[PDB]
Length: 167
Length: 167
Image 1 (cartoon, rainbow over the protein chains, first blue to last red):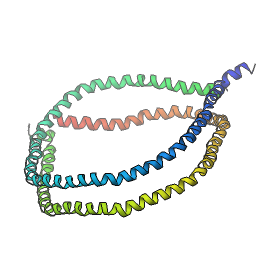
Image 2 (cartoon, chains in turn cyan, orange):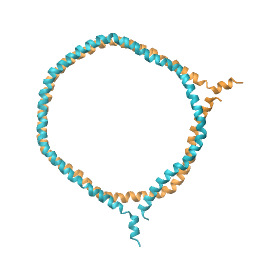
Image 3 (cartoon, rainbow over the protein chains, first blue to last red):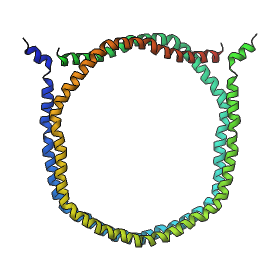
Image 4 (tube, rainbow over the protein chains, first blue to last red):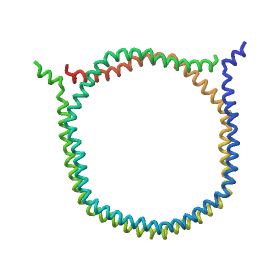
């Protein structure tokens, strides 16, 4: 016949897919409704709060800058002044110790470049030596191994397509 | 002999590499020196500028908040007040037009899901059909082609290592 087989290959799963999804998705409507209701009831008071916020924030803004802005600004001038006076001499001293730290570190870099090279050169020499014969078999096995994983994925897309196509 | 050949395979290029590099890199010292000098001569005036900045910025800070802070705070109250009064009704109206825009758009999604599916299903059906025979030859050529590029890189690392190793 051309019914049981046609339907089987047709793929009825798709129907339940969009049907089941859309069915539960319908709830989205209810959710939005509730949100709106809360937004309205909350809006009422949310308005008084916003305005009441700028009111207290406004008077507190200038009322805070006076005492704070004055103490902070004042303390800052005196704080920086002293720090600067001491930072003046310390600046040169620190620069000397720091300038030497960086320069000194670079010093070893000169002799380290040659020594390191000999180390990295010999290190790779031995490794590469063993990697030669190991790579031959390594890549060899990858051929079939990598194909196994690919074949599986290829069968999935080919199978899903064949069935989905029906014919 | 064991000189001309030993040196040739040894790789004298490395010597000129670090030598030439370090040679020009030496300039770094001079650069740092100049920077320091400029930092000192600039520091002198940079000090008066920093302090003179907080002085004018301090008096201008509060002197600006008075006129500005007042206009902004005042204008903001009258600006928001009016905007809110009109936004009250417009809010609901807009929500209606917007709520319908999103919902309406989703409407077509229901019938589009089925129609689109039939389109994407048939589209891949034909493509995959031709991709089958095309993939066979596609991957076949990739074997040798991909190997050509790999071989080149493999010869570089193998060549550089062999010569660098000398022995």
